[PDB]
Image: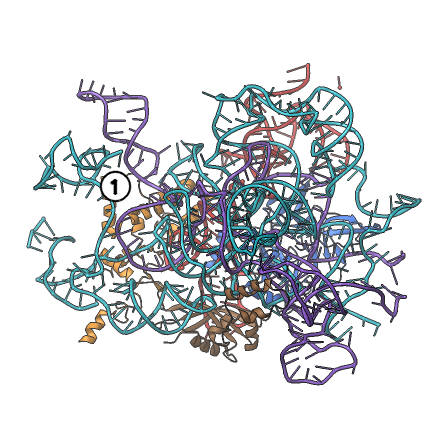
Chain colours: A orange, B brown, C blue, D purple, E cyan, F red
Amino acid sequence: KSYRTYSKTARSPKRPFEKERLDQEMKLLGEYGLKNKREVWRVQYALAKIRSAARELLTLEEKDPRRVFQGTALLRRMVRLGLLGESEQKLDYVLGLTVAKFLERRLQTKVFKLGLAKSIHHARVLIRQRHIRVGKHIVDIPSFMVRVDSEKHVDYAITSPFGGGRPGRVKRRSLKGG
Amino acid sequence: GAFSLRFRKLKTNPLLQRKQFGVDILHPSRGSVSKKELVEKIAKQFRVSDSQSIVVFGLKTAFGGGRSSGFAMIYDNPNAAKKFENRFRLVRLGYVEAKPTKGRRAYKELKNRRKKVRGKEKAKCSGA
Amino acid sequence: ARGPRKHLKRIAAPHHWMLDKLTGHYAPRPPGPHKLRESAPLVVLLRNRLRYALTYREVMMIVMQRLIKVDNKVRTDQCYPAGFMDVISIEKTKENFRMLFDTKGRFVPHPIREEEASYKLCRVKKVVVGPKGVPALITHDGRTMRYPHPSIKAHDCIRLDLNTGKIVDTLKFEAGNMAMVTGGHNVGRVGVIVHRERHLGGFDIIHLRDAKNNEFATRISNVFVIGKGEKAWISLPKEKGIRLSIMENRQVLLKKQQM
RNA sequence: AACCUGGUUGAUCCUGCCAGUAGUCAUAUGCUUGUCUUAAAGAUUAAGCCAUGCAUGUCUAAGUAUAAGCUUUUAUACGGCUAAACUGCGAAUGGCUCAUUAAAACAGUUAUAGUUUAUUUGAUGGUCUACAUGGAUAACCGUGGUAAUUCUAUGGCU
RNA sequence: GAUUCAUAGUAACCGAACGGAUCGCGCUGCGACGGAUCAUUCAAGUUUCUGACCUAUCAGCUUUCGACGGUACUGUAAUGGACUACCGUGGCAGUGACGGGUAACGGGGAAUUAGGGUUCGAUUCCGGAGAGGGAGCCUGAGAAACGGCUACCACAUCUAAGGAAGGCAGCAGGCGCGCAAAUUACCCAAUCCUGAUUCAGGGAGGUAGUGACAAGAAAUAACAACCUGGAGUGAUUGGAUGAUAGGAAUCCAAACCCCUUUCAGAGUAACAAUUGGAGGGCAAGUCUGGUGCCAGCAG
RNA sequence: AAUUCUAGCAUCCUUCUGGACUUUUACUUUGAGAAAAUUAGAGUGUUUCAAGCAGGCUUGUCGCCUUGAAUACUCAGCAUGGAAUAAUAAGA
């Protein structure tokens, strides 16, 4: 009845059990500090939208007015998102993307890359416990993905102990208790 | 803790005898802003006569806190503001006391009984 | 079935109003001078274009002041179909709005001068003899002007006076006369008329040429003569009905938003 | 991701199915369940059957006021405000369901020189006691009938 | 594009239709209502062409009682075998007529990871049909109406036994069918609609409750110092956010949730993650007890 | 200069001032008209995201961006440029 669209962000692979596949996915969990195999398949699916878009465009012709429009819009996203570097703007380059390029751009890594978090796991806990101001307002969610002008901007939230606020609750219990 | 006011989307509306605009407000430290405190500050900004001309609604604090934004609507006179504005918006402010009506189910049960009696029907009013 | 439908639904509304999907199950339903899908009701001007009203309630509170007029006449109904080339006049503010088609294919109230807001154009649907052997035009608006010139034929516009009833300035329908499109794919585009094909049976079509030398076609029902070969009786909206390209409309828009 | 593994033989290469695997923004069902956002839900079989309550009514300066109604202003036809009732308009929209139905319906595409159209918008029109024609009907008052209903009769006004 | 069209003219016809016996604010303005013809608009009725699932263990259908056509009525809002008189003998079919089946309303669409396809579409929009089964009809611009009426049939209510009234495939709710589906809740505030209408009404519609049908995000820990040494372990102590419970303001038609900020709020972080497997296919133990072609597993 | 399209000249119509003739279609090209929702898709930090169609600048007050909400998609039917291919017609 209600006019609300909805979609599925991921889908499971055809083979359940392959030692080639399970090993290479487990590295991506171990590097970037992920909860479960759905978080990989999300990005697996998200790439294949962008990849199948370029695969459709690249078959045609460089002077065709569909490709010059829809290509330049797609390349703007990859430059904005910090996914493809700006030195190469060819549509061909989008194909040479991998899942490691997307997973380095999410906020788990860009905290750690920043280095405030120290360790991949710690960085996820800092995000979820209401620290880390991205731009103007604070962000609670690991799978954010940063737009490259915004990346310098990540900093501890004004509120909170790292930030310069009330020291949570447990430090007060020690301080008032003593 | 105080707050910083800064309006947006202003539209002077002489047909309706009122000015409409989104407020935007910045409040580091403080948790939210009450409308009784906001209507005092927006009065002295806009150089108004009477608080009762002004009426204010919406106000979501954004995610994180510090920032918030809402709607507002400065009339001229309170008597013009009482006419054109619906009563529920005024009531939160408290300019006008709430009107105690009877229930919707109770009112419906009168008129179906009122169908059955022709002639003088007004004995059904006291009977219900 | 069984009679005329009193409701219209959102989504089943016209797209060129640009009523949203949420925030209502139904949409306002406009019968008046103009058709349902070749008009826009007076509510969605006030709330969803001009931004005077917030709600459907507030439009009743505006219109029952008797502040809104159209064609120097007060229309009290909130769901009155105000269509192509109608003047709107509000006395408070002292500003007037002639409704034209935007280049994208939308209604927009184009603001105009006080002396210009007297007159308006009406393209004649046909010409026909009434009783006592008197001649009579009929318009797209559904007016019926009577005692014209013998000059005036079908498919051409006449400047009405409005302050008085009578006609003032004719126009002819020929090659080298300015012409806006009112419907179909090429709506909101204005160009000189190159040529028309006859096709003796049904549906005459006209090829015509934009001021940047783009050539495009429409049926004669959609075509609406403004004025002479270059120049125009009326004031035009933003872009003057060029309709620049898809990549151009991208480039101009994102260049704007960076400020 | 334009994908393939197990099973006929002492063993091999085939045809060939069976089984495995994955999806459903498809139902049902088992065990488990901390949080917030959005949200399908008596379709499948019984278009089977229904207690009770509710879902269609409506008044403006502008059709008709002698409530034996109200209200302070005090009006020789009529101060306003209004129950009730007559008149007008609506009730043919909306909502629900899928049993019918296979060039039927429906879809896109014509035609109406083969026609009706409340309303809206714009036109038109002296040509047939004229300082004003007629008599009944509610509500209301008096009064009954019937076990019982949105049953209503006789009598008197306008 | 095209007429016997518009329109004018001539000769008469009928009453069965218009040419205002109406109302408010203020020699004179404004608009409320009524009604005729002509456009106009919201429509509706017919109508051209093309398009569909299975079935030939359905091959010949249609007709004197309209089947195909012709003339002249009649009837309709108008065109028509739509209907009636006479007259002709046609029309459709192997490119599937006629008949049967559908666990068949049609389409816009949905699922399905090359391309081509296959299956689904009761269900948000647009048509269509129906209000237990059939049929008939009044009023009106419009209905063969069912929250209108008349009748039969099938169910069923009250009766003082003469009679009277009923139609939830509207919203809740109940019985019954089943593998299979929610509250007899609050309000017109939003969205629109009807009316004599700025004001009244609306189970249309919206808000809440039930809700692992479904879609999205992501807790169940992190970091230190103090054995394996070529970064991982080790309940060894150690100090550093919401689940929850109650305020504040905000939201709301009135509650409620979200988002803010608040006093309390974890050390086997007892605030304890389960569901299926471990011969092969299929990722993962020639482990240890019990059972002995038994019980059972096993797609 | 490649790649498009087009006028002439090797004997190439004309009735006029764009259409009539070239047998007829299919085919292909461009164009008309065809509701939205859904689908792909332009733009935009709903905190991310599924979504949604919003927003964004700013001590200025007839606020501005003469604000955005693009566009595609929708056999048979109507129209049109064209030299092949294939039907089809014919045979002053």
Residue drawn at x 79%, y 49% is: C151
Q: In this view, does B101 lie above or below E93?
A: below
Which of E257 and A96 lies nearest the eye of the viewer?
A: E257
Report x, y in % for residue E116. Answer: 45, 32
Report x, y in % for residue A81. Answer: 36, 53
What SS does tag 1 mark? helix
Q: Is residue D74 above or below residue E155?
A: below
Q: How many marks?
A: 1
Q: Quadrant of residue C203?
A: top right
Q: Can residue C52 be seen in this view?
A: no
Left or right, residue B37 beside residue D11: right
Which of E33 and E169 lies nearest the eye of the viewer?
A: E169
Residue drawn at x 20%, y 74% is: A175
Q: Can residue B31 be seen in this view?
A: yes
Residue marked by disc 1: A21
Residue drawn at x 22%, y 69% is: A170
Q: In this view, does A24 lie above or below C165?
A: above
Which of B72 and C100 lies nearest the eye of the viewer?
A: B72
Report x, y in % for residue E200. Answer: 58, 66
Report x, y in % for residue A39. Answer: 30, 50
Three-letter code for the amino acid on which mark 1 is drawn:
Arg
Using a 10 Å C-alpha cutoff, classify the residue at mark 1 as few (fewer than 14 neighbours), some (14 to 19) or many (20 or more). few
Left or right, residue B43 beside residue C136: left
The chain containing the residue under callout 1 comes to A
Q: In this view, does F23 lie above or below C2?
A: above
For the N terminus of chain B, which image quadrant? bottom left
